[PDB]
Length: 329
Ligand SMILES: Nc1ncnc2c1ncn2[C@@H]1O[C@H](COP(=O)(O)OP(=O)(O)NP(=O)(O)O)[C@@H](O)[C@H]1O
Ligand SMILES: [Cl-]
Ligand SMILES: [Cl-]
Ligand SMILES: [Cl-]
Ligand SMILES: [Mg+2]
Image 1 (tube, protein in one colour):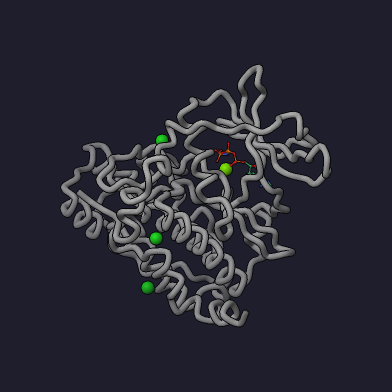
Image 2 (image 1 turned 45 degrees about the vertical axis):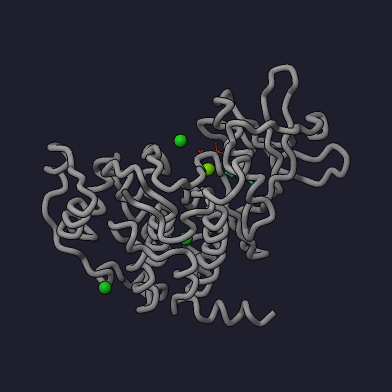
């Protein structure tokens, strides 16, 4: 079986009540202490509003969880409480519920987000280095708490470009890492699913989040988001294989003793690894550097054991000056 290279035993050492979200008894707050002000988003499982504290009027975010199973409600709540206060994690402020319908609501800090479709074309070489570093600080922290995010994507990375604050949000797909556990591969979003999700490798770890970050980083520096534009889960692996090459995919399949479907094998075919320099053009050359390619190259690997950890990534030469500006304080 496969185990994480780092933070392998966190949930083994911690007391059971840290990761046993099934047995969590929520201590709810007064639900009438908040009221919606304007609907701000939606989803398959919730409907998030810009709320407002009834007293302070101070704004917030009210994520009203739809009829989901109580086991998944407790999981997201327990993860948000374990990660509260960590660097660049969205701050859970309160947890309330109706008392009549038992419908729960998660109260978050408000973030003056700029949607990635609007913000990303205006990001510079320095902006990308800074924001990816802030996102790496969030991933390293949650990995150090024995938790995988499993839904890293631009829609879940809130950026207030005026204050240059970043917040990793949406933890409804997050899970505790237990060594040797077989997880559901129906996680994350199509364009950011790691190869392990597309080949049914169920004993994945924190490195799944590093692949998703790699897809984001590729789409940013090449100004081609989504970078792997697959039309379904099978075509997603095909889009990956024509970039990374099939010969390293075959080695990946042989190592973990996996096998592709007869149908999927016909679509993947045989392909040479494409050099990252082939994706440079006049519109994105100002964002692409040799350090950027080396850092990207060490994230997008079939074998999840060869991907950089978050801490290994923060130490890459691509982030040298960002660390210089950070240590100066
Ligand atoms: N703290 C926040 N501040 C501002 N907007 C927020 C905040 N949290 C969430 N949102 C908005 O709400 C949207 C969806 O919230 P989210 O927590 O991802 O619910 P969701 O149902 O899990 N979405 P999904 O990825 O489809 O499952 C985001 O894309 C933002 O536009
Ligand atoms: Cl799940
Ligand atoms: Cl290259
Ligand atoms: Cl990590
Ligand atoms: Mg989301």
